[PDB]
Image 1 (spheres, rainbow, N blue to C red):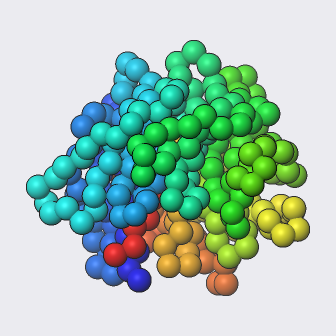
Image 2 (cartoon, one colour):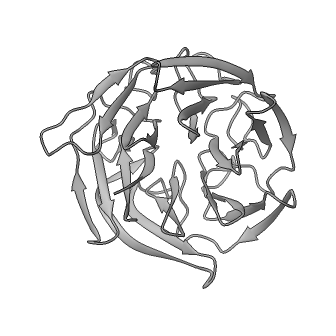
Image 3 (cartoon, helix red, strand yellow):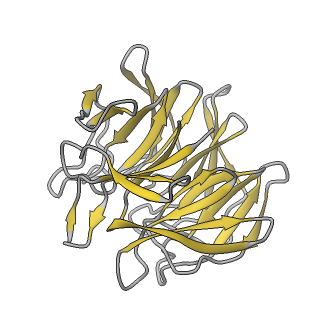
Length: 289
């Protein structure tokens, strides 16, 4: 039942992509380092599946990455990351999620173009498969699964910040539009809590945002939520033990080491901890121990 939070790579305060992987245990309220990833990767995504941490694409300062590597979370202090099949496309600032026993990765930038494509990883065969294309090409969008359906929210198409939301049903293989967010956001963090997809922070073209919105998947409608303690752009989001966590990010002035948590019943955000690193555009995921 204990869930831990993993924060992988991103952009660090020394103005460089980083390879640092930190783990936060809510039980001890301590951070620990895991073995570092093999390459420095900013604009990176991460997911967990079958107690394996996956680090997906990104940018190493020179190349956008199709590379993917994996860490078995049951390993001891002495390692070791291992590569698995690369994606079909190079993707910086892609959205990544899991549904069933498979990884879904959409959008991103390859250094030339933003992607409408989504692709899927099957661990049993170590293969990535191209799936259907979104209507709008996007980088900086989140991917989230809510009751067997994937939602891709907001982002940036190379000129415009987007408030558009698309959903993908594995049963149909099609993307269709749903009701958009109030505010256009790129680099917002996204997670599901109760029956609602929460979208936290990001950048609206003008300002770095502390604003939060929640989408009722049952009623196709958006509502404003209590704002974060601070603006956070290129911020991670996930849920540990029934609470929404926002991880690190850029506040418009500095990179952040803090993590803050939201509880809908008391309707409050508070900073609960700080990592040893300040970062943005880190990948984030949760493992159950």
